[PDB]
Each structure stands twice: as C-alpha cells, then as structure tokens.
Image (cartoon, rainbow over all chains, first blue to last red; front, side, top):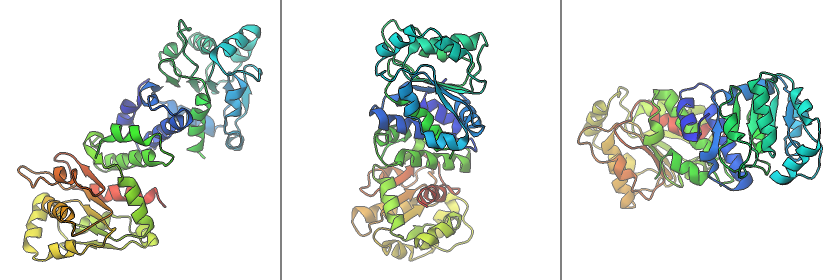
Length: 198
Length: 198
C-alpha cells in the first residue's frame, strides 16, 4: 500500500503497462477535483491494478455504497464486459459524509447486502466511512472476499479509522490517505481502470 | 527542464495526456536498459512533448548523430507521418563514446550537415557529446532552430559540458543528467513519442 513515486519505481521494469495505468488514474482524479495532492495521498496496493483487470475481464460484480457513485460509473463499458452494478442502499440524495452516515443508520440490513457480495467483486465506497470499516472487519473475519476495494470515503474528525484500516488489509485496494474523499472520486478511479482495459 | 516527479505535478491539471506520455517514455527507456535511475536522471523541458507532437504531426525531418540511432527509429510510423530520417555521419560501426568522438574528428564537414538542419526538425543525439555541444552553440547563436533536441550521449570524464549546457537552452529538449547515455536510448525516447501519436 504505497504512493505514486514508489509504485512507479517498481512498475517500470515490468512488461505490463501498469505504470501508465497508475498515472492515468491519478490524472483522471485530478481532472475530477482539481487537487494535485492526490499524487501523495493516493495509495495503491501491490497487485491492485492486476487484481482489478483480472476481475473486470471476468465480468465481476461491482458494488457501490450509494447511488451517486454507481451513476458516475461508465455503465456502457461495464455492460460490454458483463459486469453488473449494485448499491448497498438506494437513497437518491446523498452529497456529504453526514447525509451518508445518517442514511446507513436508518437502513437495518445493508450489512446483509454487504455480507452477500460475491467472491471476486469490486467494492467501491465513495461516501460512508462506517461502511468501509464494516467491510474491513468482514474481510478480516473472512466472511467476504472482493477482488478489489476502492475506499475513498470522506475522513471526518473522530471518524471510524477506516482508510487506515483498509491499508492493513490482505485484499487489494486503492484508497486516499487523509481526510479527502467524496465527490465522484471512487467512480473516477474505477472508470480509469475500465477505460484502459477496453 | 525538470525531473519526473516535478513534471508530473504540473502536467496532471492538464486536459492533454502529457503525463501518461511522459511515463510511457520513462517505461520504454527502462525496458531498453533495465535501470530505474532514469526516473531521476531524465529531464524534460516544459514544452518538450507538445513541441515534439506538433513537429511530428507536420511531418518534420529527423536528424540523428550516427546510423545506429537512425536504424533503431520506428521507420514505418515515421514514413506514414511524412518524416524523413538522416544522419550527420554514415560510419556503420559506432558502439561507444570513443568510437563516436573519433569518427566525428575524421569527417571534415559534419558541422555543415548540422548547420543545414531545417527549422522545425527533431535532432536526436545518442552517442557524441561534442556534437551536442556544437548543436547547443549553434542554437544560442540562432543559426539553427530544431523543434526538439533529444540529447542522450554518454558522459565521460572531462567531457564537453554538453548535457548540462542543453538544460539551459531555449529550445525544447529531453536529456539524461549525468554519465548515462548511448545504447538506443535516444531512439527509444523518440519512438515513445511517435507511437503515442499514431
């Protein structure tokens, strides 16, 4: 789980184009939010790219936390690959970490839907830290086994240590160290991996 | 001129894919020589990629110092663009900085061929520091005006300060700070820019 400069170092003596893909992803994130810091804050695990491509080529399920993340996904490219897209809740108005944490407090069985995610799924969490925390716990206990976790919720003061907990996970992941998150960032990240595949 | 990490910083809030192109070029260099240091040593100037693409799209002439550089160029792609390829000398056996400096000492009129390079041409120097130095001098005096200079000669003890002199040039350029050079590196660099255009 390392930064741009370090990743790039070890990916350049590779036959694959993982270095080009990594910088494409950073570029797309910066074009979404306008913040060059993400070169530092963004963290990919070794084998994140490879696990992503392998899962996408096999037409993996894709699960997002909330609808706005799903709706920003490149839906037609994903359909061509045979990937289906689902959300953990259906609330149409979620724009902040507070609206998200509130909404995941009302629904009584989103944890059920998370627990049922198919092995090999891509899990993209753009809004709610508590959902990312629950995902990390289920992974540790070996109840779920996604191919990839994209964890880019917003970080708030006294948040569930979620992004930091994801960095210790044995599951391939991409995250944003610190309090940056939300917007469409999680969807942009996944889109960058989709568009460099087809 | 500036390194990888710095270039990348200022190229990410750009609409164009110059950040992806830069990392592709680094990647190709590392696949040619196997040396990850070039991330540090390689230096691009601010307008380098853009000037390259503009000149290649216009079917610019390409001039190399020696045949082995020309022969490593992607000849068919360049022909499709309308770019011609020429060399400053025709010696078929040049493998080291010594064989190159020797050969540019015998020929009496390579400086004439250099002085004649058309405005807007791409100049790729892979072997001889003294040729790069002469090129820098002609540029300062405004006798020649290439669109781009790729300067990747070998750096030897008490060499003509050439690579360092190229970094002060007003002409867009790509070079390798320090004593690394030769092989096919100059040709690989140019090829990376050609293949990401067509």
